[PDB]
Amino acid sequence: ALAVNAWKTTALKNAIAAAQKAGDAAGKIAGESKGVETIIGILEQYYSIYELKGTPLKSFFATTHYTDISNIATVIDTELNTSCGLNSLANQAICGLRTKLGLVAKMVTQKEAITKMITNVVHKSEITAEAAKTEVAATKTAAAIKMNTEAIEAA
């Protein structure tokens, strides 16, 4: 069976490349979800930031990308200033961020500490997203190539 093995040879090469692209597609989507999910989790537990611009973080990160450090940092810095000045009220939740950012003199502005904090947070959420992408891509690829090889070897 010369002609039979020749086409199965090409079929299997294509099945491999298809199962990898199927895995990447699924992992890419899994990564995006996991990244947004991770930054929200960090800001809420570690920094008790539960809203920005009057809205829950889930809504905020629909219009601001979770990796957009410069935008995220500016919004947090602006919100601290408008909510936590001497004319401000009510012990707003975001005001606690100042103590969490180690500003006391032991030389960093508030905006600089926030920028480093968010850079740190975004880096952790990107690599956590990358891990989820890696797992989901591998699980899908394994299941796809197994299914496809068994088909070609049985045809």
Image (cartoon, grey):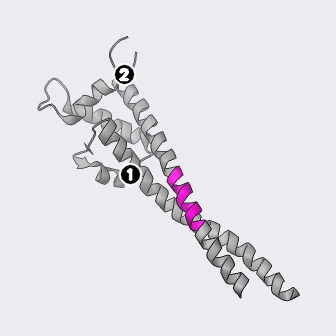
Residue shown at the point (48%, 61%) measured from the top left: 29
Q: Quadrant of the C terminus?
A: bottom right
Mark 1 touches mark 2? (CB < 8 Å): no
Q: Which residue is mark 2?
A: 109
Point out residue 68 in the picture as x, y percentages from the top left corner. Answer: 43, 44
Quarter of the image holding residue 143?
bottom right
**Dot 1 crowding, Cα within 10 Å, few <14, some 14–19, many 20+:** some
* Residue type highlighted by circle 2: Thr
Quarter of the image holding residue 80?
top left
Residue shown at the point (35%, 21%) measured from the top left: 102
Query: Disc 1 vs disc 2: which is toward the camera?
Result: 1
Point out residue 67 in the picture as x, y percentages from the top left corner. Answer: 45, 45
Q: Which residue is mark 1?
A: 37
Question: Which residues are drawn in magenta?
Answer: 131-141
Mark-to-mark CA distance, 1 and 2 = 29 Å
Q: Is residue 65 visible?
A: no
